[PDB]
Amino acid sequence: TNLCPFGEVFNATRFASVYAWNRKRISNCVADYSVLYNSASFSTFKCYGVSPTKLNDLCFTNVYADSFVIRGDEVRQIAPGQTGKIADYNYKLPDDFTGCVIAWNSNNLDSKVGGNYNYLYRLFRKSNLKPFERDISTEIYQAGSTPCNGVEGFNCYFPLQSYGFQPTNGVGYQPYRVVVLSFEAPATVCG
Amino acid sequence: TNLCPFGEVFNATRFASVYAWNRKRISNCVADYSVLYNSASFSTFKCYGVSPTKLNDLCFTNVYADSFVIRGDEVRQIAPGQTGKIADYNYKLPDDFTGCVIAWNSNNLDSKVGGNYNYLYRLFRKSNLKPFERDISTEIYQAGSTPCNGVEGFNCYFPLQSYGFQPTNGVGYQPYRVVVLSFELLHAPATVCG
Amino acid sequence: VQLVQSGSELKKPGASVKVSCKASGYTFTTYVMNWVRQAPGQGLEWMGWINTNTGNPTYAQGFTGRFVFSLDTSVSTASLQISSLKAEDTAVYYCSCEITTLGGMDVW
Amino acid sequence: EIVLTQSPGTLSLSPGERATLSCRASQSVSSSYLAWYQQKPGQAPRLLIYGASSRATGIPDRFSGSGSGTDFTLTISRLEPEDFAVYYCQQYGSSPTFGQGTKLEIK
Ligand SMILES: *[C@@H]1O[C@H](CO)[C@@H](O)[C@H](O)[C@H]1NC(C)=O
Ligand SMILES: *[C@@H]1O[C@H](CO)[C@@H](O)[C@H](O)[C@H]1NC(C)=O
Image (cartoon, rainbow over the protein chains, first blue to last red):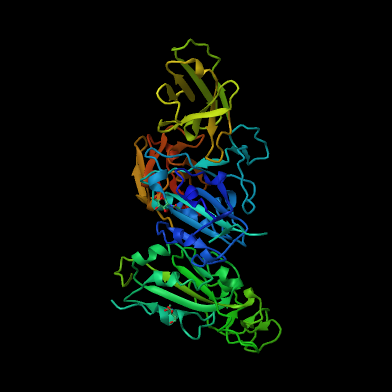
């Protein structure tokens, strides 16, 4: 009857880039969802397959909390049946997704004046990612018939770019902290 | 400082077919959105482009409450950038949608034992709908090079089919009442707040 | 990605010593460099980390007042300076990276 | 969406002089997706600048990019005869969009 450590995921001082996304495992604890929901500090809080106000009265065998930082225009891609560089090459939800996605503007925390190139995304891949796949590979991407062998140049590029987050960026171009709650034997996470 | 007639849309006794959806136009009233979402009576309450709890502290020039009936399987399609027979031929949300989709199961109200065929959807159409397009044309769909002239038969079919809602249908094959709240912008003056 | 440190150091008590930690392969100011200490017959012990952009160091309790993390972004080189060496500071010293809170301590 | 507005529509200068072509974006935009292209009469476009200020290979020093936010400028330090062509600018959100094009002719 211990509480769930959600405050350790959301209120974490620093997050991870979307291509190396984080996954916390939640078990053997109780969670008050509508308290996060009544928080009213988020810009997006959209679930699928269930209701946010009915959440408190449910259980699951396991709950997974996935967190990263993307860009305002790309939050729309963290949803079932979506396309784009983030949805295809970084983080994909299955069509039968039965969870919630949460986001808020984080320009205050995650953008440096000269430029905070700490956050990265995958830009060049040969095929989309499976649902909940994670690709950390930094192998040089081969766009030509001639192979690369870990040497950049023509037809051989680094598959990762950096987000350019400046405080003067456009709102769509600002950094947004995202959290995803997946819902899934006896149950250990209730309310 | 009059309260909005959201009760008149949500608590309406008979809803519409999905191909012929309604647009109650909301104007000049105060809306307590937080009264609606804490209702906990909805199996789907998924906004886009705005936060449900931050909604009380906001204003818009016009609020459009679109409401129709579909199955639970198709509730997923009342979203931006969806495909499927409802999303393509009946009710399409724009990829820049900025409102809320609300849904709840209606198998108690909207299903008769012998079968209730009152509700309908559009099964045949030559191209997808534009965002917020309503198509009420009952014109015989032409499938061949040979025209129809209002006579059913081969390659000439009625564009509309009927939902078969029975209380013993699967939960996905059950009726779900949808209310779609579309929010506009300012520039022009505002009339709906909280 | 590569991390190559400086050579062994013999010093008397009260002396000082500066270890270096060159890197190669990636963008040096993108990621964090942190230090770990392994005394003889003990386990690993986390010392702290320095932000490679802002320069802000963080010292875990016990490594404050005599230890200095520093950088030279002209040569992608992290450094560890210890003032007023004691006999008990005898240990192996590792520099290491942090992809993320996830990829924490991936390269040594 | 993003909409690009080049100015002026027709820029007239003699060989040698310095050319300042303008590209204007309808909203705030990342300097990391903005490219410049050159199109001589009857030829496929040529990539000149990418990102915002980076010369693509094969492009001489006389070309140089700049800008941020909503205004960006292509700059040809010293014009040459083969530089008299139409110049387009690109930006890109979910999908590419181009500008109307600036014609650069002899004065
Ligand atoms: C984060 O910290 C603030 C301030 O203490 C608190 O109000 C908020 O509830 C915290 N969030 C979570 C998820 O615990
Ligand atoms: C519908 O009627 C019930 C019963 O009076 C009421 O509690 C509920 O608030 C009404 N719904 C709306 C949207 O007014």
